[PDB]
Image (cartoon, rainbow over all chains, first blue to last red; front, side, top):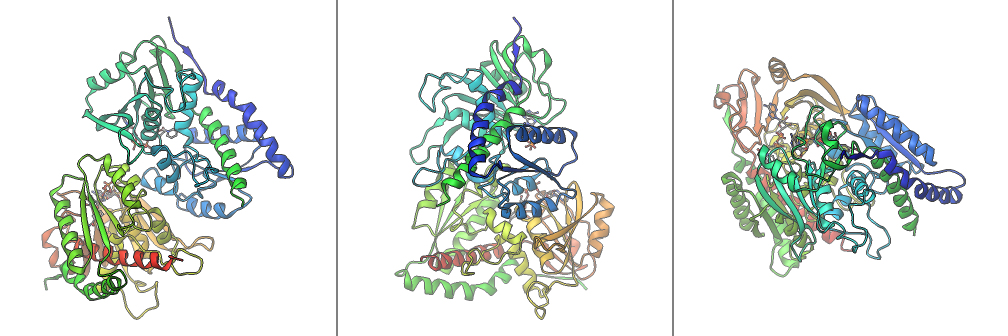
Length: 317
Length: 317
Ligand SMILES: NC(=O)c1ccc[n+]([C@@H]2O[C@H](COP(=O)([O-])OP(=O)(O)OC[C@H]3O[C@@H](n4cnc5c(N)ncnc54)[C@H](O)[C@@H]3O)[C@@H](O)[C@H]2O)c1
Ligand SMILES: NC(=O)c1ccc[n+]([C@@H]2O[C@H](COP(=O)([O-])OP(=O)(O)OC[C@H]3O[C@@H](n4cnc5c(N)ncnc54)[C@H](O)[C@@H]3O)[C@@H](O)[C@H]2O)c1
């Protein structure tokens, strides 16, 4: 029996009602105006532009004052971010990567004012995710947000009902096997960790080697315990994936193909890469298939902003 | 006439007297004990171990309580850093890269407690270097340190007398042409920038393309203006280098060779890569030749620590 297909939009539909209401309350207190979310586009990519347009329309639709400040020359994007940080009118900032396409982007993600960083690119949010820190302040008022991409995927699994919503917080994924074909510091590694923290065993795939992320094994630090595995062998990946009942993928290659033999029956497949790295025939094998995150990522990024704003008001004094 | 050769040690000799005296004053106030500098070694590299030993002996020699906490499995190095951050006894922390050998190391460099980060790996010090910020606080008490590697190279040039010590601060390199064969976010890019900020025109070389870093061109941000150049062409590099009277190199390849034809007569050559990327015959062409930074980097890293400590006492209330 062929597997169904769930669109990112359908998942995002769920959050609309929640997000909207939060914005309305904001509008009251802030004399009719909603929060100003700025988006920096500094790359010449049709896909990025398309996504940017999506974020634009979706946010405006909800009631956000969205501004898409496009930069010509890469190096000035930084400067733009600086004055934007100081711009009180600006309530949230996001950057459309790849800007430079290397370490620089990772530098830039640390330039955005932490309080306004809606995507959760700032290092602090990453540490907190790895060390299971829920808040920021001592008095537990300011809740620490998580980077939208992995947070979205999680929410996707929650929607798909994989997260057994009958177990205590941080263990809903107990008896589950997951595999993430990506270990990028921006999404892959954090995603795998985030999953493992919820109970599931994770097979983290990388070009060089594979690893097995599991629950924290220390008392000095509540961080996921990594179990290193054999060097990247094609047939090895197969074995790992076959055991995994949940597979996530995010390889940048526009011509990547995840062998459908690897997919286990009933396996839930999710792709976050801006490209189609999944082989079409995957439908009959996977129980559920989500072609691309995108729209879901946007919803999270938005609600994250709402949390940041609430945090600003919460830390106003 | 063949060019001379200056050893990193000889340069570091200069700072000994300064560093020592600062430590003695510290010893008084802190009942005979000097500052505790911890070094995390988590890589299986003969060179790194050798360097670690050097830092160990040099610091102890000066009067620093040096501890070399070696970690077996990479993933636990992080945890070690955390408890070390909280360890009040620890006055400074440094990490021996490559730990993981990828993005992770860049993640880890942001895990070290900013106040104890002696090498200047933390993002804040990088921003300040790029935005010419001298201090941290509003009242201009806490001076912001710069990452030891590029800071060392600068000090090397200051020693070599390239920095015309008769011009006002931040313009001693005015009529000088420099080229940096490295654009790593950790050293290359910051170094080139740091140089340009002092007046000199910089040719930043990368595997993909070359660029021309120059003085700040904006009023909204005091950041060096980058002039992008043609894609990396071998004979192009030649042209750039020929104009450059000062050449710095840091390519990781143990078998790299910088064609001596590129070197201009009287050109000052410096290498910071842990490997010999310079062709031996370079002596007759270059006016001065510094084989490797190492020892100088250590001295800076040390004095940086002294500044951090002074900053801690300075921000005690
Ligand atoms: N949907 C979104 O909102 C969103 C957000 C962030 C990232 N992304 C996607 O993720 C990509 C991130 O890649 P990057 O720029 O960090 O590049 P990179 O190549 O440095 O990292 C890619 C990661 O995937 C791994 N990978 C690459 N080829 C692989 C292969 N053949 N087999 C197994 N693993 C492989 C790499 O080892 C690495 O861990 C982006 O290009 C984008 O397409 C999408
Ligand atoms: N002496 C010290 O204390 C110290 C400190 C930091 C770094 N280092 C050295 O610098 C290296 C940093 O490299 P990385 O790990 O970031 O690796 P990487 O390959 O990601 O970056 C190396 C940088 O040099 C450039 N480069 C590489 N090959 C080149 C070539 N053939 N021609 C021109 N440019 C080239 C790359 O484009 C990049 O900008 C280290 O391996 C180490 O050897 C030494």
